[PDB]
Image (cartoon, rainbow, N blue to C red):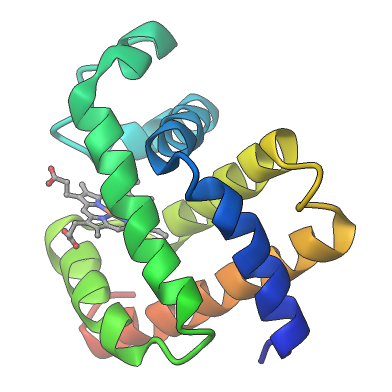
Length: 152
Ligand code: HEM
């Protein structure tokens, strides 16, 4: 369970993400797909993309990043009270998309890496620990929903 102070560190770096969520999403997705190419495999709409240049030029990838980051931001803004938001996300990701929890950890690592690089002013050590705590809680709760939905 996060403290209010930890939530505020999460939300103050998210405020900078929101200056340009599309650009942040491109960086995060490119980082994810380069570090863990198997994640890109899971995304039939994007898996043809071969290079970073193609990824930066893909309007679908950009839109994908905006949708994903905006849904994560809505979860973070609930400061742990995110049961309603996780229900549909867990169901689609466990049952249709078939995204293992480990791939959500990979995505979490890409988020942290990009915030660290782009936002040293709001992603110092304490802020990065708060973000990690928030993403671990997200992953914990969505893993519990995965199990309830019949996926392990
Ligand atoms: C914080 C983590 C994530 C969030 C908040 C998130 C959010 C979303 C949202 C809002 C959608 C659209 C509605 C839906 O289908 O549920 C979506 C679709 C999708 N997501 Fe995720 N996602 C996350 C992680 C991932 C990861 C790591 C992968 C793959 C490695 C993934 C694969 C997909 C796919 C394949 C779709 C459908 C894309 C299509 O329409 O062609 N998601 N995600």
